[PDB]
Length: 109
Image 1 (cartoon, rainbow, N blue to C red):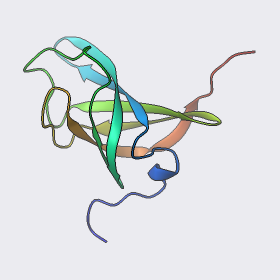
Image 2: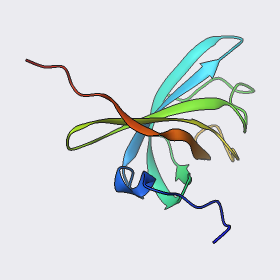
Image 3: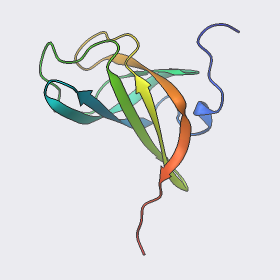
Image 4: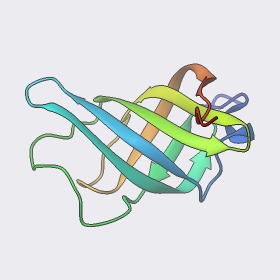
């Protein structure tokens, strides 16, 4: 039902799994962190950082383009996204867009 649903995202992402957080910092650089999920509802997840390595103030925003990455048993499933609705410098949503492809695959021979 129309409640910002998902498709196959929860085949790769999970409610307690963790994701990279590549934030384009258009004025600064990038800020590329880690957070665990706490709640996953289709295209939407909610996050809690991983540690005291947190961004500068005023810098995160609710529609920052941010890109996620998680490993699930075969490749790197990464997805571009937006923040959707921030809550704090360490607690925030994300909304997956552009589908999740197997971009990377731990190139170790």
